[PDB]
């Protein structure tokens, strides 16, 4: 439950008071996921969901403070409110699960116990709500309005176990899906939520099938297996500062940024590539004096993927690519998307991989065509003059092509083809000819850009791609096969 070491830090009257609770919690042997989720969820409710300060409520108060260009009001997180909310969740969990019926084999949770905790959270939810609704991720949401998004159900099942005393049960994460790891060596896996809009009830099953299938959703096995400190990182990354689609809460942005720096300094972001990208994103908006520059952090997110996850992740390269696209750095952006397709090349496109398909489809047929049209504008009184850009674009299509190989459903269709022709066309034949497409000559070493295609489709297209006159039909037909 809630002990004095936690309660004496209440009331949380400012942002620094929230960072203080989190600092203290990250120093305990077992940081309380429930209390930290409800707290984040309480400040988020008043800062983004419902900003209209209440009149009927007497217990609730707000804290004035000077805003940066009058006053800014903060929801005072009274111990009273939060404790009641904490007591509600524990009682609900404890009252539903009877651990005397489950035999703990020397501090080890069994599948049958895990699936029950999973069923408890699952059956507590409302029958009809929008799944992609913002701010339904925290435990505050689960208790106060009983709504949880896909990844939020997984964290609540981990939260609920820690309440029951189950320590071996941890959050498992890919780049678009969440589940649970448990057992005597943390090698047992279990599905606790749903993925996408409309699919079978995989809940309670192993993750083994998606790993062997070579789907991006299961990251060929190199996914994150969180410890308590990483589960806190997820929860912070899950703060949503959006008030609406155009405006965001400055305090929620400042909060998340302060929290990420706390987690970072303690080394808890070393095995979390996307949190580093998020930190960089926020550092570009409001930079913190005496801290690494966004690019340094973007590159730390990639470094983490390379070291701890066999370079099998897409988004650390997407985070960098977004940064360059924001600042019209065409070669640096095209380079990062080419790097992205180099990661996806060794995967196989499955039905459930629609989130990253939509991602590659937009860059190949909306974002890249928009950067090159803007580059063509500037040309009338440089990237289109750079042969290296052309190699990056070519390397990007090589990636999608290799991805399609061995996959059940097609990736490339008639819609992709026109934007390849059009994008090739933005590069002059003199520029395109400066790129040498070489298979290789001699293997290893003995004691004008060069490019090597890893896919059949692009290898067959070699001569057409470099030709002064682009044979549209031949490139369209070859890419569509
Ligand atoms: C030109 C273009 C430009 O700037 N654009 C287009 C590019 S892009 O390269 O197409 C591009 C860049 C960046 C992204 N981002 C998506 C975001 C990454 N993450 C993925 C995980 C996700 C989840 C969710 N939902 C999640 C779910 C399940 C399991 C998980 F592991 C994570 C969140 C759940 C709650 C927390 C978690 N977040 C998290 O782990 O870290 C934050 C969050 C989003 C990177 C996409 C595409 C950009 C510019 N001109 C127009 C000027």
Image (spheres, rainbow, N blue to C red):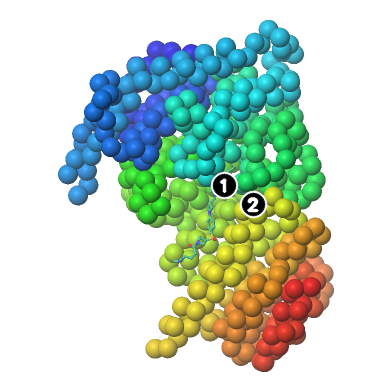
Find residue 413 and report its horizontal and vertical position in percent.
71, 70
Residue holding disc 2 = 313
Residue 285, placed above or below residue 107: below
Task: Return the residue found at the far left.
Answer: 70
- Circle 1 SS class: helix
Q: Disc 2 and disc 1: Cα gap in Å? A: 9 Å
Give the quadrant of the C terminus: bottom right
Find residue 295 and report its horizontal and vertical position in percent.
47, 57
Residue 427 lies in what quarter of the image?
bottom right
Residue 151 lies in what quarter of the image?
top right
Q: Residues within 10 Å of mark 2 (few under 14, many from 20)?
A: many
- Circle 2 SS class: loop
Residue 164 lies in what quarter of the image?
top right
Question: At 72% from the left edge and 53% from the top edge, which residue is drawn?
Answer: 351
Is ligand 1 closer than 8 angstroms to the Cβ of mark 2? Answer: no
Find residue 55 and report its horizontal and vertical position in percent.
23, 28
Residue 61, placed above or below residue 193: above
Q: Check whether the beta carbons of the residues at disc 2 and disc 1 lie within 8 A of each other.
A: yes
Q: Which mark is residue 393?
A: none
Question: At 37% from the left edge and 16% from the top edge, which residue is drawn?
Answer: 7
Does residue 23 appear in the picture of this structure? Answer: no
Residue 140, placed above or below residue 324: above
Find residue 71 and report its horizontal and vertical position in percent.
19, 40
Question: At 39% from the left edge and 26% from the top edge, which residue is drawn?
Answer: 21
Residue holding disc 1 = 273
Task: Return the residue found at the far front.
Answer: 128
Q: In the rendered view, does 293 fall on the left or right side of 366? A: left
Does residue 320 appear in the picture of this structure? Answer: yes
Q: Earlier in the sequence, mark 2 or mark 1?
A: 1
Question: At 68% from the left edge and 47% from the top edge, which residue is drawn?
Answer: 217
**Residue 55 vs residue 209, the one in the foreground:** 55
């Amino acid at each position: 439950g809630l002990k004095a070491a936690q309660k004496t830090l209440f009331p949380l009257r400012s942002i620094d008071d929230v960072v203080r609770l989190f600092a203290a919690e990250l120093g305990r042997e077992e940081p309380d996921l429930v209390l930290l989720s409800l707290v984040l969820g309480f400040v988020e409710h008043f800062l983004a969901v419902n900003r209209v300060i209440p009149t009927n409520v007497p217990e609730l108060t707000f804290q004035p403070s000077p805003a940066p260009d009058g006053l800014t009001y903060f929801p005072v997180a009274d111990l009273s409110i939060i404790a009641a909310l904490y007591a509600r969740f524990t009682a609900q969990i404890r009252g539903a699960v009877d651990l005397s019926l489950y035999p703990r084999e020397g501090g080890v949770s069994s599948r049958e116990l895990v699936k029950k905790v999973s069923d408890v959270i699952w059956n507590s939810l409302s029958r009809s709500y929008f799944k992609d609704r913002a701010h339904i991720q925290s435990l505050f949401s689960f208790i106060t309005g009983t709504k949880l998004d896909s990844s939020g159900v997984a964290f609540a099942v981990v939260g609920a176990c820690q309440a029951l005393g189950l320590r071996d049960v941890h959050l498992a994460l890919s780049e678009d899906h969440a589940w649970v790891v448990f057992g005597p060596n943390g090698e047992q896996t279990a599905e606790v939520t749903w993925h996408g809009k409309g699919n079978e009830d995989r809940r309670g099953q192993t993750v083994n099938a998606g790993v062997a299938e070579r789907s991006w959703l299961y990251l060929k096995g190199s996914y994150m297996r969180c410890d308590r400190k990483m589960e806190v990182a997820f929860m912070v990354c899950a703060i949503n500062p959006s008030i609406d689609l155009h405006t965001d809460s400055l305090e929620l942005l400042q909060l998340q940024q302060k929290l990420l720096w706390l987690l970072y300094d303690l080394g808890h972001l070393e095995r979390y590539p996307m949190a580093l990208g998020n930190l960089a994103d926020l550092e570009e908006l409001e930079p913190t004096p005496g801290r690494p520059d966004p690019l340094t952090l973007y590159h730390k997110g990639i470094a983490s993927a390379k070291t701890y996850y066999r370079d099998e992740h897409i988004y650390p390269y997407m985070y960098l690519a977004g940064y360059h696209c924001r600042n019209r750095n065409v070669r640096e952006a095209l380079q990062a998307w080419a790097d992205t397709a180099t990661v996806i090349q060794d995967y196989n496109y499955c039905r459930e991989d629609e989130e990253i398909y939509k991602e590659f489809f937009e860059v190949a047929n909306d974002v890249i065509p928009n950067l090159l049209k803007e580059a063509a504008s500037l040309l009338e009184a440089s990237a289109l003059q750079d042969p290296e850009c052309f190699a990056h674009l070519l390397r990007f299509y090589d990636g999608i092509c290799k991805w399609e190989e061995g996959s059940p459903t097609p990736v490339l269709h008639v819609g992709w083809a026109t934007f390849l022709v059009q994008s090739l066309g933005r590069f002059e034949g003199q520029v395109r000819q400066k790129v040498r497409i070489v298979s290789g000559t001699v293997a290893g070493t003995a004691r004008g850009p060069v490019l090597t295609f890893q896919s059949e489709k692009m290898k067959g297209m070699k001569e057409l791609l470099v030709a002064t006159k682009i044979n549209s039909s031949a490139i369209k037909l070859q890419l569509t096969a």
